[PDB]
Amino acid sequence: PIVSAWEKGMEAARALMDKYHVDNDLKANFKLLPDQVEALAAVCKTWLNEEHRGLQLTFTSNKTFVTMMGRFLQAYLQSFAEVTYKHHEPTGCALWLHRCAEIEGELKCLHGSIMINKEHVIEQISNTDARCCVHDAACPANQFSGKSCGMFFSEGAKAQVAFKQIKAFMQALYPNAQTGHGHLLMPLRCECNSKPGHAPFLGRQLPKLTPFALSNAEDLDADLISDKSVLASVHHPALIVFQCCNPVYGPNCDFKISAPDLLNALVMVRSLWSENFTELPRMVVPEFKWSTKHQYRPVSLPVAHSDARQNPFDF
Ligand SMILES: [Zn+2]
Ligand SMILES: [Zn+2]
Image 1 (cartoon, rainbow, N blue to C red):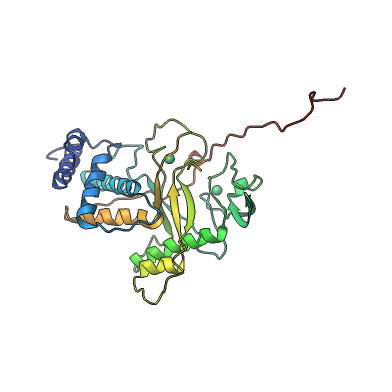
Image 2: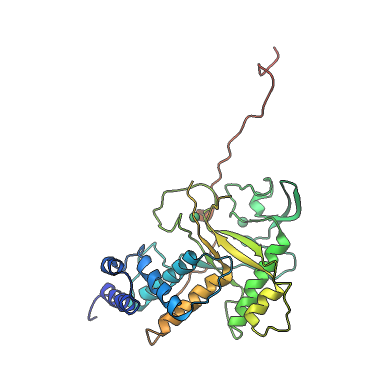
């Protein structure tokens, strides 16, 4: 082996970084380490500008799309050179066999068990079609137990529409797939937990999963469209959107990417790669498995209710 795995990785990365004009300091300081994603994301950004200036993202931030590209590029780099860093899987993602578009009206959470119907009233809007993790079956809507996977939907039916969207999006891009149509590509890490030794935090332990309506996609005329990808959204006008583990309406971040854009980050990195290497290495995004490590970490604190009385008890 002419040069080590690490030296091989490094030579491929430097080739990329020179070809794409990355900042000199990013280049100088790049050492192929597991948290060094910024120089690779700059490769990706520069290629986007050069080759895909009009790319339209939907419920996705520019920065998150480009960072995910960086992560997927990091993964192919590490596979090319055969370098792995134990406990630092590079993509920060997983493949969830969701089963949320199999049965009509029916959702399943990360545990793989069906979600229970709840009422969720917000203030005043009455959602009669909420869904909770079965472990949260006795909590108020949108409160989570120590056994929760963290998943809740205020509107079950819109959630299912978003899962049908991603499934049809995948059918359109892989019409002949033998496998993977029922899998969701999902991130396991936002900025808050992108490093394995990050400071522990309370709340949800995985990027939040939320369906967003594409409210104008119905005001659209289906007959003019032949692109099956686009048709997935016309027929199912809602997107799965991933945000921070604990998005702010503890740490929190601006991570935001829709499921189709996330898939696109991977597909587009496969194109960047093919313009630079003759073969695409094997690159395995882990299959998601429920484990107790992903449990919501609630803090349930009693709060006193007001009593006009001076004294607690009559004697
Ligand atoms: Zn669950
Ligand atoms: Zn976050």
